[PDB]
């Protein structure tokens, strides 16, 4: 596997890879255009998301938005994200239908080795994130690498989600825990 | 009641209401101008806040700032907010005199039904937030819908405030709890 | 001591001091240029960081970035910060070599008196932050005033660090606590 294929697969890779580096620049060019767009340039924002993402249909994302690659973000139907969300998509971020992200939600797939030498080596890795259908993620929440969230979940504002979340629950806290069953 | 009146009152409403939709666009036009203003355009920033907010006198808000409507934000005298605060003002956000928000404070009045069908219906609601006099809210804190904060409160950085806070206390944690009496 | 010298030393000072006020405007002018720079204006961004910081060699900082003064930020070699980090540098922020900040990391040295009258007086203060070598700070973490972080530390995403962190540990939670020894 190439560095790019390894990255997507959740294997150790080098981000300084030429191809990945070019990909990151392209994403940042699209995001710069998105984030400076005039309030009324709805149509442009829609075109940019279709150019950026791995899959999108209907999506509404309040500026600002940030991501690493774009092409590793796969959205189901009728997606909404409020102001200033971030998706570090080194591995796939798969989001189901009718998702709502509140302001400042961060979703991370990127990680580094815990060992300092390994970390400073230029080697890094990722773990994918999968989110089901009808998920509402409250403001300022953090979704960590390798997490799967089921269907019909509510993530409370400010929650830090470190482990999988099953269907039909509310989770809150840091580390998040189940606080209510639906 | 109209959808707008219901929204402000904390009843279920539809954000796709024509009037609310126009109101949101207007707020975003003002916020776009605010957030791109040159470092030295103090005077313009002052004019924009007087056009945006339900009430303001003396206020200093570091860009960026974000909100939903503007007109549901009511500030007492001598207000300060540091970089990149967010106020989702579907219901009134009432803030007393001499308040200080640190960077990245989020105040939410907006909420959704916990039930997925209800949530996907287009119906949503809010609960007002009221903050007293001489309140200091530390960086990255989250103030949730329906919370009242009393006078002379300190909210520690990163606190997630889920319940009312009485006068003359320090609160911290997620969910926040009292950590010191003044 | 002057208000400026007091500020840097972690003594009570008045931010409305003429010199400090001019310094803040200069920092904001540089940050405005940084944050609007085109995706490809790498060279400009490098020049701006060398003009802004108290010390920098090799540094890569994704826009946006925010700070108070600039000159109180001292970076060791091979520094990286991801999107939208904030450093309130009223006192020195000293960061060692090979540091990595994830998106939205906030580092605060600024603080206010807990007493409301003291706080509203215009008097404020700070406490320095020192971070060692080979530190990785996860996304959305908060580093509070007066904290020292040792070498080879991992700060988990969303951690709120309120006390010193010794060498060779992982810390997480709010308030952060040790969750693993390396």
Image (cartoon, coloured by chain):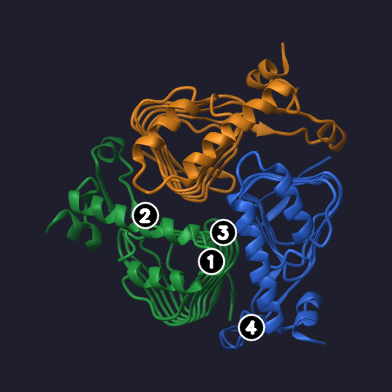
Chain colours: A blue, B orange, C green
Asked if badge 4 and badge 1 are on a common chain, one would say no
Label 4, label 3: how far apart the Cα atoms are:
24 Å
Disc 3 target residue: C140
Q: Chain of mark 2?
A: C
Percent of width and height locating residue C83: 56, 62
Q: Are the two marked residues, 2 and 3, in contact with CB atoms closer than 8 angstroms?
A: no
* Mark 3, other Cα within 10 Å: few <14 / some 14–19 / many ≥20: many
State which tag comes first along the sequence, 2 or 3. Answer: 2
- The secondary structure type at the circle numbered 3 is loop
State which tag comes first along the sequence, 2 or 1. Answer: 2
Percent of width and height locating residue A111: 66, 73
* Mark 4, other Cα within 10 Å: few <14 / some 14–19 / many ≥20: few
Label 4, label 2: how far apart the Cα atoms are:
31 Å
Q: Quadrant of residue A129?
A: bottom right
Q: Is residue C121 above or below residue C135?
A: above
- The secondary structure type at the circle numbered 1 is loop
């Amino acid at each position: 596997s190439t560095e790019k294929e390894k990255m997507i697969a959740g294997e150790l890779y080098r981000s300084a890879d030429e191809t990945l580096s070019r990909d990151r620049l392209r994403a940042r060019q699209l995001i710069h255009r998105y984030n400076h767009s005039l309030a009324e340039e709805h149509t442009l924002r829609q075109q940019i998301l279709a150019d950026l993402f791995g899959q999108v249909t209907e999506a509404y994302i309040e500026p600002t938005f940030r991501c690493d690659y774009g092409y590793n973000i796969f959205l189901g139907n009728n997606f909404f994200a409020n102001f200033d969300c971030v998706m570090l998509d080194v591995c796939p971020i798969r989001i189901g239908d009718n998702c709502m992200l509140a302001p400042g939600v961060h979703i991370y797939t990127a990680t580094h080795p815990i060992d300092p030498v390994a970390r400073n080596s230029g080697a890094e890795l990722g773990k994918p994130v999968t989110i089901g259908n009808n998920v509402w993620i409250g403001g300022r929440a953090v979704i960590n690498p390798g997490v799967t969230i089921g269907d019909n979940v509510v993530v409370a504002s400010g929650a830090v989600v470190t482990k999988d979340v099953p269907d039909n629950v509310v989770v809150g806290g840091n580390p998040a825990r189940i606080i209510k069953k639906l």
